[PDB]
Amino acid sequence: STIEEQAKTFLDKFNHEAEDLFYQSSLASWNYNTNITEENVQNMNNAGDKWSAFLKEQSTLAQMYPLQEIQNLTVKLQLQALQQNGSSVLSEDKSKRLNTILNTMSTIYSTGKVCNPDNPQECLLLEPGLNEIMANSLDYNERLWAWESWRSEVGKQLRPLYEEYVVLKNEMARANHYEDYGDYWRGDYEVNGVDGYDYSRGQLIEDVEHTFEEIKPLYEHLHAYVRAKLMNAYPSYISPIGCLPAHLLGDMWGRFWTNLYSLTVPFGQKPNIDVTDAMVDQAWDAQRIFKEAEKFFVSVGLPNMTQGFWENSMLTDPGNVQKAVCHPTAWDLGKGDFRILMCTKVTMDDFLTAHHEMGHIQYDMAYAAQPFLLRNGANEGFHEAVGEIMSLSAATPKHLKSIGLLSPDFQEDNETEINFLLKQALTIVGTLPFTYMLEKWRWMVFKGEIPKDQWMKKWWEMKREIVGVVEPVPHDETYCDPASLFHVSNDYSFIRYYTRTLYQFQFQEALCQAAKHEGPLHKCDISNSTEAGQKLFNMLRLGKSEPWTLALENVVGAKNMNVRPLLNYFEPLFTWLKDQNKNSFVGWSTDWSPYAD
Image 1 (cartoon, one colour):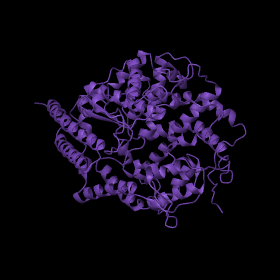
Image 2: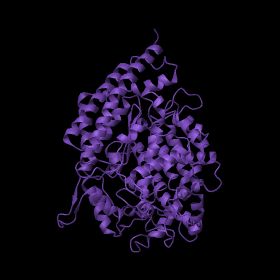
Image 3: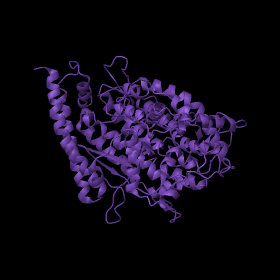
Image 4: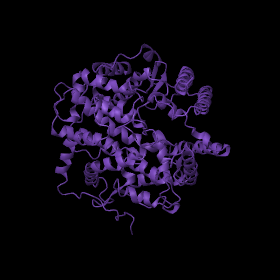
């Protein structure tokens, strides 16, 4: 007879019906990506449309209950994302236009081919095509062609479409009582009604511009080291004084710098750590790799994974008889059912991605006690943070020796950790400034901070200022650089690739403090210590029922998100580049331009 009892009863009819349909829908998607077939493609389409209709019905039904009368935080959290109108705020023409626009977004991206009209042989696909020539190239113009030419057509046919995209989504957000779409993407770190833990959306920029300011030193030395190394490859192209060419950063955009390591090794003569040589002679396979990662999780208290998981997940490619998209992803079908999509191969990386997904698996299986709407990451960067630390404990030599994969007489020296942390920072430290830039750019564009004529001049002006790379040749306003990314074209949030980074280091620091690890943090490990696993599981079962500041408190003890764990992690590395840069130029100047003639 009261609004709060009615809301709870509605939530029971919701969670008792929504899971039965989402289970069926996720089953259809899993079946389609297991059997790439025109029979399968319509199955997960109608499965998704059924759930899209059901959630729209529940969204228009749940708005009758006011949120100003509810006092239970769980019910308020459940109703908050459900009473959100979503795309229904717009007119029918606007809705159809936005769906068509989005359908065109990734259409141009995926079906965007590159070819040379004068060189028929200079034709190649994207994966394992276009990415390859950006991944293993030592030539300058061989990268210039595949870099400009990629956004020559794809980076142009998205400029006005993206202009329409931004103005439709601005009205998408504004009709939601939001300032801009950037303030809608900051909408899930938003917390209301919690005293001392209330998290305003605008505080994200305050946190981000602050936390980046202490990374900026270490990243400046890392950029200086890579530049001081790079004239070995391009002595006639790059000024050691100026910034870097963007086409020489490892791939199409520069997100990951991982493939830069092979030429910028700190110590080449040191035999790199390698177990790729060691499973092959040990007769290891996909089943054993997952069984072994299971012992890693069990050692810290994370329990034995379900029986049906093994009978229903796929680990090896099922040959040619059918096609299966096997990007690294872990699937939560719900209802206690969990299957993993992995093209497993005998290599550390595929072992490391197996562990990274294993983190997703046992994180996801914990909050089955949480309601359906709450069965999600505590925040958007919170899932690719929890499932990655456990990989960082799989690639440690102390772990590899504990399992016998590495040599029992394998020596680790002052030149070993430098190579290891350089490889990791070229993956984890180089990605942070570009995640920060991309989302800052999205925020200053959704705010309308920029007019059309400066929709790109500042972009290059700002990446010449934040990351420290210049353009070998300029672009005009007709171009559209950031849309070339998958997460920009397909309208995804990218800052989950910044926040996860500074979440996982806090997690690993807290856990190897709980394990009472004595030594540098990069050698920390979590295995064979139940006291850190039990600490992690207490947060892990929360899901989203509590806010992310309190989730950070539960493991680390701080509501804020900090850089201190990351700088402590790379302190052995940081001191090293302090020694290596006694003669190099720290800092950059934007006035330099390689085409400035």
